[PDB]
Length: 129
Image 1 (cartoon, rainbow, N blue to C red):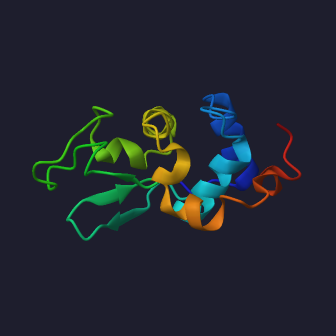
Image 2 (cartoon, rainbow, N blue to C red):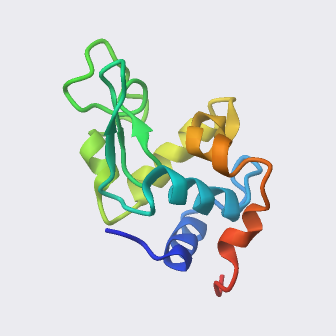
């Protein structure tokens, strides 16, 4: 599923990402835009042989099991395929654990490089939230 910007903003707010660990909703929409272009089916292989999955590109090296990342962890206790659903519940629940891990949203490279230090409020412009 390819979310609309305001559509995703509404879902993320409903699942309680607005101000989670102090990150405003705009931060989460900006990250999803530049991690996945708001596409829940996005996947990307990493050099260490892990893969990134879903609208926030959650990595199989730590957070989920894909059966092909030997010696990896599964800290969200989910198959990585759960992270590609049109239902963002599993991605939000896993993102809350990632952002709580003590590096904040720096765990998301696209956030760090395209969102951090920008006015992320722009990402919720025009939405009825």
